[PDB]
Length: 121
Image 1 (cartoon, rainbow, N blue to C red):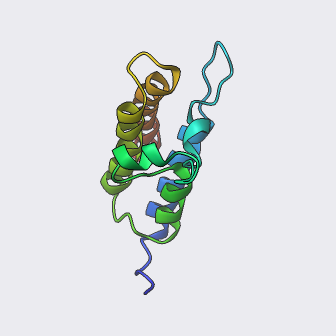
Image 2 (image 1 turned 60 degrees about the vertical axis):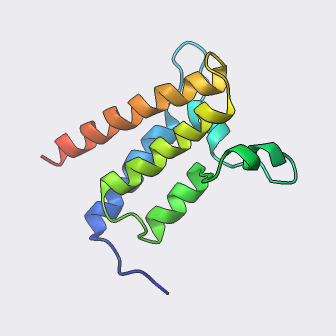
């Protein structure tokens, strides 16, 4: 089944937010924080990930869920981004590069969402 499309301005805003979060780079090192979250590792590769993380998500899935109108609100989108980051914090250890990048990405999402929505008045 096809879902009823969101209003196109809502879709547009979801896309702009996710694009900005994905492109965000650490200023000192140039590292794209999101690059490790684009594509989940396979269950073949990393079976233990799928033992611990019950609802995996990556940015490929998030973009899919935007395109297919699964998210009906920015709150819906935000929850999946926060879940993506939660999962990173469960599977990786506090103080690790990947854990700490996921913490920053939570704040980037919030800041980017607000910039975009304030722009739209």
